[PDB]
Image 1 (tube, helix red, strand yellow):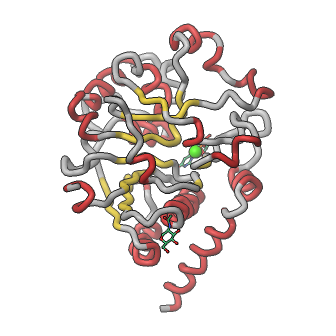
Image 2 (spheres, rainbow, N blue to C red):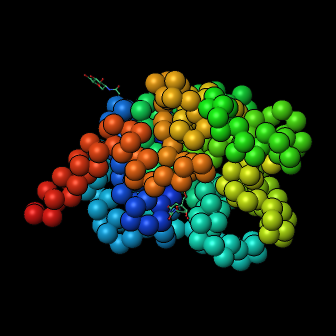
Image 3 (cartoon, helix red, strand yellow):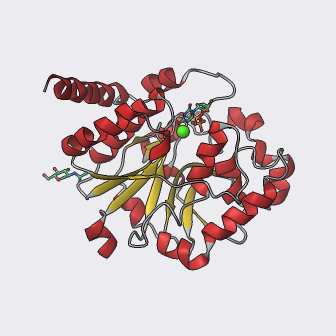
Length: 284
Ligand SMILES: O=c1ccn([C@@H]2O[C@H](COP(=O)(O)OP(=O)(O)O)[C@@H](O)[C@H]2O)c(=O)[nH]1
Ligand SMILES: *[C@@H]1O[C@H](CO)[C@@H](O)[C@H](O)[C@H]1NC(C)=O
Ligand SMILES: [Ca+2]
């Protein structure tokens, strides 16, 4: 309750790089606030954001009734760098969970910038982790026609996992008290540093690292309904989805905004609402 009183009942962080992902990030935030009456604070990885986004966030905060904070954490010099901006952004999602946030914050949830929330996120804050420092949803198996693209069901990953789930990194709850209690941050940084000496390792950096460490840094497998993506999940399970991720479909390669408008009926409503707020602020 000290964390809830000082920060908020729900604390969410995200990362966005590019005007398209910033546009989706405002939509994600509006979707969270339309589905909760609990207090919310959004945390941003500051250095990737545009000046316009950072100028607009106080307007979003006053319109939607949320608190916010910008975190600017410098990549430690000892730790192997990522030349590709995509991989550096993935590093910011998983390698610094213990240092991005204050010691007074007990829990934080990563929600992808391209996500659409359809649930009260305080349900994830209250979800029992049974001692795990973090919880991730598994990758769906329900869309049977995409089995050939489930790389984790054969080869390296099938042997490595021994039947454990291969989790998606679009959404994850981190019990920061337990993550700190376990030294998970230091351990994830040292494993990443050693593994990344091979440039063929950790292809999906943010996702592969926690899945690789799940025998020593436990993952609480969240209910499947916490994360639904069309690529892997059946149409039939969309009605149960608490959140939607617009993940890439390797079979169709359909553009991001087309996936958003086609799959999510309320997407244009949030987009037009944020554009209406922008026009209202611009005149004044
Ligand atoms: O903030 C971001 C996140 C992703 N991308 C790019 O968008 C593409 C698809 O990545 P995305 O995260 O959308 O894929 P998903 O994980 O949703 O399947 C890649 O070229 C990324 O470099 C980007 O420009 N900005
Ligand atoms: C918030 O409270 C109002 C009170 O009238 C209620 O109608 C609404 O459904 C609540 N929303 C959530 C997400 O709990
Ligand atoms: Ca995504």
